[PDB]
Each structure stands twice: as C-alpha cells, then as structure tokens.
Length: 73
Length: 73
Image 1 (cartoon, rainbow over the protein chains, first blue to last red):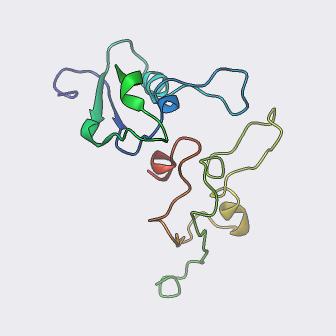
Image 2: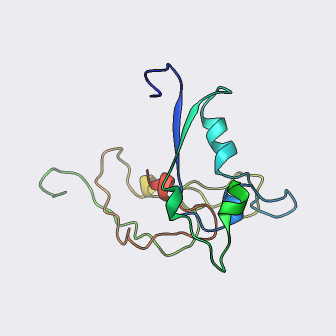
C-alpha cells in the first residue's frame, strides 16, 4: 500500500511493549530521557503523512509493569 | 565455517545488560560514554570482513530502555 500510494513506510512493532513510556516519552528532567516510538517513527520518515504499521496490537500486555493501551487511546 | 573461508572470529554474547545503550552508545556530552559493542568488535578485529557469532539471542538486553530488537534489526 505504501509503494502503491507513493508514500513512505515505517512499521512499529507492538507486543513487546509493556509500559506507557514507550508511546509517550519521559520528561526531560530524568537522565536518559527520549521521546516514545512514535516521534522516532515520524523522525525516520521525512514527511507529515506517511503510512505506519502498528502490528500485533492484540499482544500488548496490561499488568503491574504498566498499561500502554491507555496511552495508545 | 570461519576457518573454511579465511575470516576471523568473535563472540559478542548478548543478554548481559538490560538496555540498548551498548549497541548504539551515548553522546560525548553524556556522563557514561560507552561506545558501540559492535564498534568495539570492529576494534578487536582490524578487518571489515569477519564473521561474528552472537550468543544467547533468545534472552536479550531488554526491559529498561526500548528493547534492542530494532537495534539488532
């Protein structure tokens, strides 16, 4: 679909994600703070309208480690 | 396999840390300035050719930063 529409592709792999801070970032105050997967994705492509594949969205986990679906909302 | 094709040999033995900072390092402004564990492997060899064995890839250096899957990719 990306090749057919002459756009740019970048896939983010969910499923391995376990906390909120991989979708949003961390505040700049902490050390080793960087934005989440999605601004990295928008940086890799150069445009404002890419296609982005978020595969295995049914494999995100919700437990004591975190809850990334609420940040995905 | 390496001696059959006149390369050299290394072991890089992944899983021992729990971050993605050993593969791609941190900048000179940061306090801990650990360079690339691939790049130090390219230091231990003097050749751009060599075969590189990667021990223990099922357990990886995950779950404190972003997981180093795409780093391996």
